[PDB]
Amino acid sequence: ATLKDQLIYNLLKEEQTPQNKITVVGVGAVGMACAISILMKDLADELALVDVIEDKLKGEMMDLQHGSLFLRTPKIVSGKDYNVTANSKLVIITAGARQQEGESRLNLVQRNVNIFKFIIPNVVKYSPNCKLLIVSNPVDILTYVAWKISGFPKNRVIGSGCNLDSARFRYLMGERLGVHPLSCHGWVLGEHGDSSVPVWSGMNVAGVSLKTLHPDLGTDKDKEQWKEVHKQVVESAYEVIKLKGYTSWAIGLSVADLAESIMKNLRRVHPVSTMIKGLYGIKDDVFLSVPCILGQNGISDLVKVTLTSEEEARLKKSADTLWGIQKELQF
Amino acid sequence: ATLKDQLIYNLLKEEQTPQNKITVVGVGAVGMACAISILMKDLADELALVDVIEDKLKGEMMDLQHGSLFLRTPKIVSGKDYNVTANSKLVIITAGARQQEGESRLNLVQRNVNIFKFIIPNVVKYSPNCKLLIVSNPVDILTYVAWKISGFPKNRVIGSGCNLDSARFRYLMGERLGVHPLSCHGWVLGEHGDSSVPVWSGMNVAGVSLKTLHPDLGTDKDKEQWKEVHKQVVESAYEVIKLKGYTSWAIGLSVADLAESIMKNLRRVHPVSTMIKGLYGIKDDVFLSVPCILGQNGISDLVKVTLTSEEEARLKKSADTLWGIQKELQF
Amino acid sequence: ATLKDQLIYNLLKEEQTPQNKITVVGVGAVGMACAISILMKDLADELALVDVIEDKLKGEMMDLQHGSLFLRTPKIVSGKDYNVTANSKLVIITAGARQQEGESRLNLVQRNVNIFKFIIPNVVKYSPNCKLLIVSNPVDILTYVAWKISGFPKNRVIGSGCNLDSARFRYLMGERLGVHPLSCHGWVLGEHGDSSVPVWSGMNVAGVSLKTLHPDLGTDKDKEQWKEVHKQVVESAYEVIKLKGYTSWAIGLSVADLAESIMKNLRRVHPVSTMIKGLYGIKDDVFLSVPCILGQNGISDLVKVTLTSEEEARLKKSADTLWGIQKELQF
Amino acid sequence: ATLKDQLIYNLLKEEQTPQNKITVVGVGAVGMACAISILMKDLADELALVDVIEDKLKGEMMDLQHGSLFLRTPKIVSGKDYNVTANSKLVIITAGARQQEGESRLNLVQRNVNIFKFIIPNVVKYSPNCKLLIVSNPVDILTYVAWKISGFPKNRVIGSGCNLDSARFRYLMGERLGVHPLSCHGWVLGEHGDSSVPVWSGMNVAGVSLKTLHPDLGTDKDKEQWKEVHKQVVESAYEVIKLKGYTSWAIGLSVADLAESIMKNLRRVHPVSTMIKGLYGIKDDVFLSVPCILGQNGISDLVKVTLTSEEEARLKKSADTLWGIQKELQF
């Protein structure tokens, strides 16, 4: 008789379906930053890793597995075959197109659409009742792409959007005032990138409107130039890529935070990208970041923020752009 | 329009069942010590409290409910009715017969059976696929009672047993050697109480057999009298009960540790009460503590500890006692 | 040679001062809820318990000790003598008379003033650089008493204040809007009691002013009666005491939350009782809850919350109330 | 009047040193894996990064700082100048030279000695009371190097040693037996690398000696080939490097586990590299992995494992080889 059989008597052989499984698609810096943030927040009873490069994937899986003693996630799996993702509660797409040197914006988006025409159906086939969290950039448009291809209802297709943008706003707001980011409140909404909207009205410490105190907050006659905070937020990624080549930990921590709200059904509010037709004067099938309530059904609700004429027109101008690009995409 | 509807757009009202629900039956010191431990280890997306005293029950629920801002458990419910326990993954029974000043063990058990004849069928009705963790004393006998009434297979009926007895053993072992209890290894097996078997052969730090180093370990010849460590484990509950009237924190943390293993499907080894028929020449339907592997199907496997002839006789003698009581019970 | 000597080589004899030591004065339901909450949030490397009931005190220490296997706080000690508190960063005062059914917090003044004349000098003697977190009621005045007796600067004397009352406000706010309390922002200021001030002008989800959407909010002509939310916050403790005899869990989590911000130097904004002289035209040495920044030096700064003529008047009344009681005290 | 001074009333601009400061030297994959693991286990109130690559260093700093909202470490600083390390409790060294294809072992060590001759005195200058944790390879020798240059007593100079090796040994046990690593007890001692000693005698689940159940375990005629488990431990790093190009997460988690034991004074037993002269007939100043007790003074004690005559010879040969190298180094 075997040592295991001498040591252990077996009552039950057949294991059940995993109950709290998460898949991360793509094992780049962002993918692995999400996985380690998720593994150390104990959100999953099973982690699945998927990417097209077999050796990198098995490597990252074995490195995580070797740390098992220091973790509470008892099964970590990987493969190029999406059968490993079976029965995921949450699937996080970080996989994208490696940006070519002299291509157009439209080229980059359509190469990502071609990768998504493979990933999304494979995700749906093995985890048809899962929430999709789109991290891959450009996040607003690729969240529309994931939506169309998957055929999922709008509540179960979520773009990481202005979540990290808003977390960076609160960090900078915190450094200017000597207050921890947690107690500094402020919202970056609309299109993730240069044309995002800082909501100066909702920007507050302890429910004290910085706009009410300082009427010229966020204007050009602003002597304190608080515009430069949103300018810093919107230029942050560029500055970090400049220095270390990429961004890793901040997005990893922010995606783990979103996963926590989903997996534990918290109904916390996050500024994430959601199909926004019929709201803020938008009449096209586009995704924009607004405060969304995240739980086990994904975006169950969203907050209808009051916006100035300027801010209304900026969200509408971002939608014009996104719809413009989206009708040129080949599905 | 309501402030809520002016503020929030609803995507879907559709509500779902609890995904990681735990129910604690009994809101005495032990039951509430399980609740706060479980609540502060983020093991559940929903917690249900059930006891017979409705005001006490609504007090504890409300007191926990007010801590929500500082918790990651979005739903806390309570009720006399077991419809609030519906869809529980794990159900912990702390409720039981109040110990009469002087009476036989045959009588004390039978008064607990009459209680489990109401508790267990209700639990089974609203949560048919759940795992039962029996904490109520005498834990070994009342785990057999739960098994019989429920009709559940032996894998999904677990008694806390010698799990805390072992935590105490490893704490005291730690004080003697000045090492953390985590790095002190020792096993209390068999019947929870005075008759429990301390396995001296398995007592070690860093895999160094103390029994080999000190052959007298656990004998009456022992110069350092290590039999006192097990004696202290056996008399620990008595000594604490004498000082603060009961035990709370140690059993709450130990059950939460069991709950972690079950809910997160860790597959750790805890010494818990399990149907031990066929093992150690035991011929009767008795439950005793042996090292069991605990996951999302409860006891998947148990460890066959090599015991001395003396150690076997003590387990067989405990089985003759418990079966002697059990066969004279009325269901 | 002993088994311990045969097993372990000693390199150095213990020559180390406590580094992250929290003391809890009082082993009542409040004290032990603070204790377990702090132990399960890994905030301290030494927990010292002090009270006047030597049996109860030793029984609680032993019960915490018996679950050290499941904790990362290696040294738990107790004793009626305050030399156990030596070299504490944070001493949490929960000892003294607690509210009986329907009894005001302002009816515990003279009893707990006497108890603070014993406790505070003893604390100061053994930990003269420690931060005082006052929890005993009436907490606002007893914080002022702790300040006067200790001679400590106002930054190192903190009261639990409206931290829990504010936590409760956001919980009930959350049950109305179907959002997690974490995403529901709103401040209860002034006395931790019946005279507390709900600042309607600061209440927001995602920086959207509820007062601006719903101008009637918190007035008698409000058809949704949002004033009943603040009423519930005031009545909350009375309700819980009536239902289970005391409040323990929620204040334990509220206090561990304040302990986290202090011990980890977060500089988070908490509504805690501090010396409010010079602000809102208050001239006396009054202690009220206003939003404060909490770190390892305690209250480094506070937020000047903008109040409506109505709000400011209602806070000056809460101030007047407490100067009336404070002015006639003996030291 | 600036917005900040309109919003916030300052009491205390007086500032103090951090209390639980950790410094990570080297921002490679290993140092940054330690950084995130330490940040996510809330072990520090200040994290200082120090490397020679100023752009990469500032890049990694900013990437952690942007995730501060999701962290409880309020100050993260970076610089080439070791004045950012001032008042560190624990300084983790991951910086050093990688062996070149032709390079002799002696020459590689001497290149690290020259690097350490700048790093260690700079560390000692700004944190003279700190614990050194040497992760840089070859770990056993560079712990000796760091010890020589620092002038520190042997308790405050720790090599990460066989901590991960042993953690890998317990994973491989776990998969073979279908148990969590936490419940699988095995020890890898001596020189970190292909000469490491797997203590077959100390191999157990629930204190059952596997060597005793299976007499042939760890020998050549072992029908189950358990010797192959140690071979896997010794090759697993080479196999992971071959697949993903380096080792990252498992060493980051393993190091954070040691940081927990030190920063929180747990006194857990870890296989870490310590000055071993006087044990197993070792006459020379060599550092080898033995099971050591780790607290806030580092190695306070160490466990003397009973080894077979064969096993003592393997440590004795490791010592001789290590002294062959160290006696030839230029300090």
Image: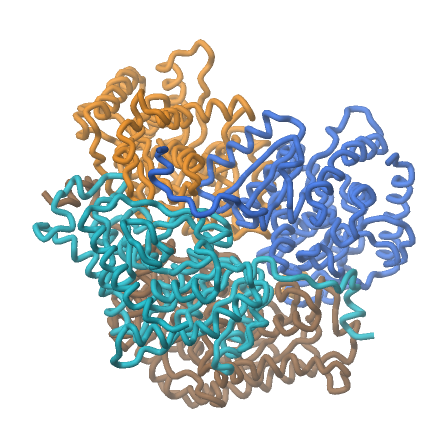
Chain colours: A blue, B cyan, C brown, D orange
Rendered view: D279 above or below B90: above
Residue drawn at the location 38% of the way across and 59% of the way down: B254
Residue drawn at the location 89% of the way across and 54% of the way down: A282
- Total number of numbered discs in the rendering: 0
Residue D251 in percent (x, y) is at: 45, 34
Give whichever of D143, D205 is nearer the camera.
Answer: D205
Choose top left, top right, bottom left or bottom right for residue D221.
top left
Horizontal side, residue D192 vs residue A323: left or right: left
Residue D106 in percent (x, y) is at: 35, 15
Choose top left, top right, bottom left or bottom right for residue D179.
top left
Horizontal side, residue B68 vs residue C330: left or right: right
Give whichever of C126, B314 is nearer the camera.
Answer: B314
Residue D80 in percent (x, y) is at: 50, 33
Rendered view: C48 above or below B95: above
In the rendered image, is residue D15 in sight? no
Which quadrant, please, contains the N terminus of chain A? Answer: top left
Rendered view: D314 above or below C165: above
Residue drawn at the location 17% of the way across and 45% of the way down: C4
In the rendered image, is residue A175 in sight? yes
Horizontal side, residue D150 vs residue D310: left or right: right
Give whichever of B22, D89 is nearer the camera.
Answer: B22
Residue A66 in percent (x, y) is at: 46, 35
Give whichever of D251, B42 is nearer the camera.
Answer: B42
Residue furthest top as drawn: D102
